[PDB]
Each structure stands twice: as C-alpha cells, then as structure tokens.
Image (cartoon, rainbow, N blue to C red; front, side, top):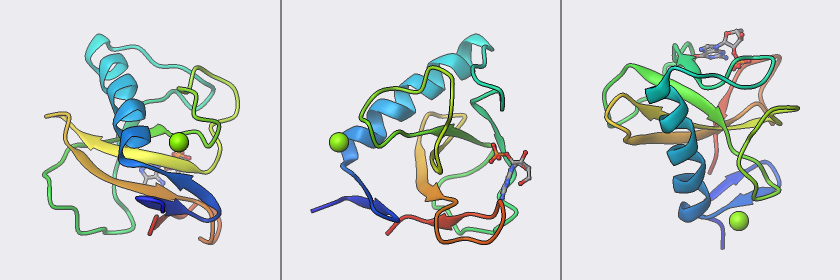
Length: 104
Ligand SMILES: Nc1nc2c(ncn2[C@@H]2O[C@H](CO)[C@@H](O)[C@H]2OP(=O)(O)O)c(=O)[nH]1
Ligand SMILES: [Mg+2]
C-alpha cells in the first residue's frame, strides 16, 4: 500500500524521507536546481493545516524513485520546514491550474 498517493503515483515514507533529505541539504547550502529553482519557499496559499511550523519549502519528489537533479519536476512535491521536519506531500494532480491538493 502507498503511504502517500499523489494521483496515480505511489510513495512510501522512505521515498519521502529521501527526497526531503536532498531538498534540505540544498536548502542549507543555499543552492537551487531546475528552471523553477528548487527547493524554494512554499507560501501555503492553499491554507493546509500542517502540524509543523513554517517557513515551508517545497522540493520535487519523483515517481521514478530518483532524486530531483533538474529537468521536469513533475506534479508532486514534499514540503519541509527549517527544522527539516516533513510537513506533508502535495501534488498539482487533481487540482485546478497551479494549485495543490494533499496526497492521500
Ligand atoms: N499553488 C501554490 N503555488 C505556490 C505556493 N508557494 C509558492 N508557489 C509558487 O507560486 C507560483 C504560482 O502558483 C508558482 O511560481 C509556484 O511555484 P511552483 O510552481 O514551483 O509550486 C503555494 O503555497 N501554493
Ligand atoms: Mg518508491
């Protein structure tokens, strides 16, 4: 079973932790990758009720299982904070425009 289901993409907690670890490291070093410059601040326009505090940052999580290194980010993202705590996993899949919905 999937710990996180983003549309049809299936992720386990380990997949999320791996992506998060990569995103946090780049965040700590002040480096970004990709045309959308990830990781970057997640403003939470959606108003999700995360259990951990902000600031929040988003980083792509890939269905391929590989860590994002540039190129197309896909529709899924892991959201983490300054304390490297996982806030949640969200996706553009099933959401209008560039909005987000949480992965189930
Ligand atoms: N939907 C959404 N987009 C956000 C949020 N925070 C930052 N963004 C960025 O705001 C712009 C309009 O949605 C995009 O550049 C988007 O980046 P991403 O496309 O990388 O998510 C957020 O809380 N919600
Ligand atoms: Mg996997």
